[PDB]
Length: 304
Length: 304
Ligand SMILES: *[C@](O)(C(=O)NC)[C@H](C[C@@H]1CCNC1=O)NC(=O)[C@H](CC1CC1)n1cccc(NC(=O)Nc2ccccc2)c1=O
Ligand SMILES: *[C@](O)(C(=O)NC)[C@H](C[C@@H]1CCNC1=O)NC(=O)[C@H](CC1CC1)n1cccc(NC(=O)Nc2ccccc2)c1=O
Image (cartoon, rainbow over all chains, first blue to last red; front, side, top):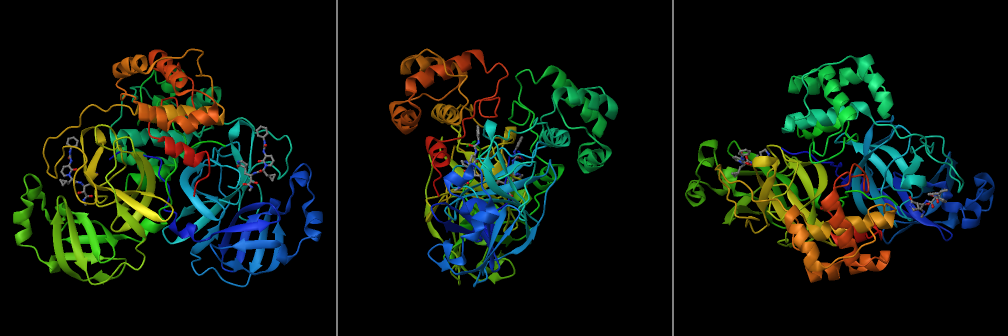
């Protein structure tokens, strides 16, 4: 049994990761078929970062300015296109190991695997969630940019994130693979703080269900509640408003544990109102909100 | 910046994972060159599990009893050998994608990546530590057995663990790739509980150093201490005795933060004696002991 923060295998993505060099700047690229994707700020100097005009910066740039390196192989750029905040570089080769793939923009609450890369080479993989504020709590050093976040349907890799910037609080922002930022952020060295970081209620309820499954159950109260009731408690503790689909979604888990959603909503309610009082649910001494109902099911089923 | 529990890329290991079927039982195998490694309890029936005599069970078994499946390919077994609690199956093919590899037995405190597998296909990867008791806190369902834990030196994969059983408390035990159990455990369905789970002191000190680096510093006290002093506090809170090498090892971190080891030993000392009082160091409301000094450095350097 047992339960951990666990990421999708990285093998399929690994072999799509290449180094991109334009001038001084060097960051990571995603190579699918004969296109290579990268953050457009690869063309920016440090003096530009303050206030860049990417179109204008693009004038002076040509195919030959972009050094794309796949291990020890210098892919020939033969065409370059900007899309929102991504650069796409047409190359003369197709990636032999392009998998079945897709670009998806995820909703806030949804989780993905992040393969961290420095110089086209992967350092590590870790799982995180798209937070309500639209930020992520990543692990990212200078060089990391152009790393991507993904899910797999054991066949088709789904690309949701590409990393661009770090923010106050030491959190992160980035783009879908069409280069639109999650959240009202821009690629610019300017003051742009995050909003209020709210907790993903449904995700916690899943974590609590995962505890029951596993055996931790001390938090299980004898009371029930209402949706309206609980949502009136939730806003006080900056949790996200729990809806009916959210209820629907927790059904299978409810099914498996024989604990109605709304009873679990009341177990949580007291934990908000009374804290864990220095006990540990599933190892954590905090309420974990970075597991989707699906993420739990994956792990309490053995899906591959 | 930011800091996460992060696992080595799984790509190289992924392509060494195969399904092994002997009778009803079906578990995972590691295929390197022309040998396939699996837990020997693949030859056990449920009636055997109670008390198995593997030698005796082996008599009735032949090369043709072991179905090794690499995706949709039925590797020909041509020789079978038992080593402690592992089965090695000689096959007529070499694994095309065998990486530079090694078998290492790790010490308690050392961490590795676990690639969880069901039916030769990987479900997920996650990082955990070999605990002082010699157990691991894994995520493992029936089917998981024969999954392996590894580190990579970005070249050479080092194999340290292969998963066999789950224990009371919902923790796990297993073997090096030579099939010797970590800890005084046997492959048998019998009563065999773990010992006292102690905390890996040095690992926590690293986590604390990772906080300072990142920016969390509220726990930094104005006091210092002694090794003997702190170790007298540690035993009370079931932490591992901190030694001089452990001090030596924390040097680079000390170097980077300009905080002597022994000052950090005093910051910890109060946290033991006073608890976090419902604050969060690096997201966790608990003292995290599953990061090696090296693990921190990797992540606060960008090693690949
Ligand atoms: C990325 O460009 C890269 O890897 N390039 C090789 C880089 C990655 C980040 C740096 C360290 N960790 C990271 O995730 N990101 C940037 O340098 C980024 C460039 C974007 C396009 C404009 N960037 C530039 C300038 C400033 C910041 N962030 C801050 O300094 N913000 C901040 C202000 C106050 C307090 C805390 C943070 C930035 O991310
Ligand atoms: C493994 O054999 C497998 O995957 N086979 C296909 C399997 C994996 C575990 C089952 C669920 N999670 C796991 O990690 N392990 C076993 O079945 C294992 C076999 C070993 C060789 C003897 N095994 C058999 C019998 C009993 C246990 N453990 C317990 O039931 N122990 C226990 C007692 C009391 C309280 C809690 C646990 C066992 O692991």
